[PDB]
Image: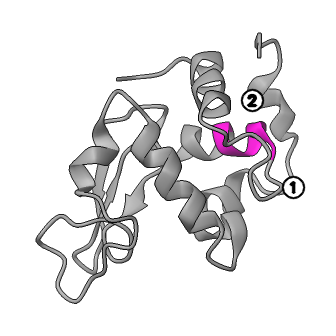
Amino acid sequence: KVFGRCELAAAMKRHGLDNYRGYSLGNWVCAAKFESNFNTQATNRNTDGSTDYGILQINSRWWCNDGRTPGSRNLCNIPCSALLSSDITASVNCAKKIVSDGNGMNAWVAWRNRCKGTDVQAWIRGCRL
């Protein structure tokens, strides 16, 4: 599923991500924009053999099981395929674990490089939320 901008903002809010760990909804929408262009089915292979899955491109090294990432963990206790669903519940619940892990949203390199410090409220501007 390819979410609309405001549509994803609303779904994220619905699942309690707005201001989770102090990160405003715009931060999450921004991260999702540059990680997946709002596409739940986005996947990308990393040089190290792990794979990133879903709207927030959650990585199989630590967070989900895809059966093909040697030495990895599955700390969200989910198959990585669950992160590709049209229903964003699994991605949101797993992202809550990730952003609580110590470095906040810097865990998402694209958030640090393209969202951090910018006018992230622009991403939810105009949205009925």
The answer to whether residue 94 is visible is yes
In the image, what residue occupies the spot 80% across and 46% down? Answer: 19
Up-down: is 23 above or below 103? above
Q: Is 44 drawn above or below residue 51 in the view shown?
A: above
- Foreground residue among 41 and 15: 15
| Residue that mark 1 sits on | 117
Q: Is residue 110 above or below residue 68?
A: above
The boundaries of the magenta stretch are 24-29
Q: Of callouts 2 and 1, which one flags the residue occurring earlier in the amino acid sequence?
A: 1
Q: Is residue 55 above or below residue 14?
A: below
Image point 31% across, 80% down: which residue?
73
Residue 24 percent coordinates (x, y): 81, 44
Task: Measuring from the top left, give residue 111's x and y in whole percent.
Answer: 66, 56
Residue at the spot of label 2? 123
Direction from residue 88 to residue 106 in the image, left or right: right
Q: Amino acid at mark 1?
A: Gly
* Figure colour scheme: one colour
Q: Find residue 30 and report its horizontal and vertical position in percent.
A: 67, 41
Work out which quarter of the rendered image holds the C terminus and state it.
top right
Q: Does any portion of residue 108 appear in the rendered image?
A: no
Q: Main secondary structure of the magenta part?
A: helix
Distance from Cα at disc 2 to Cα at disc 1: 13 Å
Q: Residue furthest bottom?
A: 71
